[PDB]
Image 1 (tube, rainbow, N blue to C red):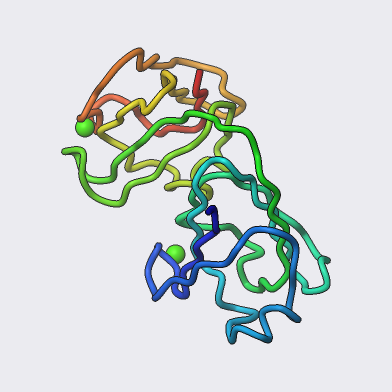
Image 2: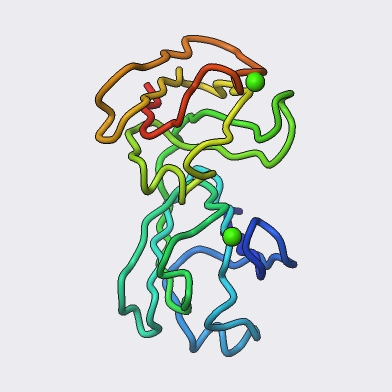
Length: 173
Ligand SMILES: [Ca+2]
Ligand SMILES: [Ca+2]
């Protein structure tokens, strides 16, 4: 019942398409219609972990995700091959764009992120705000390699766009 959902245009914009898990490429896609510069944004719920592949035929710099990716990454200039495999259930956290549990919503599973993936994997170098732990507590860092001042969000906070200065790294515990 799971299935990844891509977006034609960037910024989580542009008609989306639901593709079933499993491994496939330009061949299967040829059957559909989309291919190449199209898988701009992505949205993949838990229960499964996806792996993207720039060049078709499963080649080129690959990627790995299990949540949504408003801004995939630099290699987003070309996409066609992918690989998805079911995965155990894992809680996560939910962040909102505007300060008011609103605006572009993004979420990430438990783990660690830096000033590169995090931003280009859920939001960006900043503009976070209101957070809502969907299952695990969230901790923010104000420096690369998660090393410096921090703000451990041990609970609900539908408003935080006034403290986290430049979120360089995070740790969903
Ligand atoms: Ca963009
Ligand atoms: Ca806020």
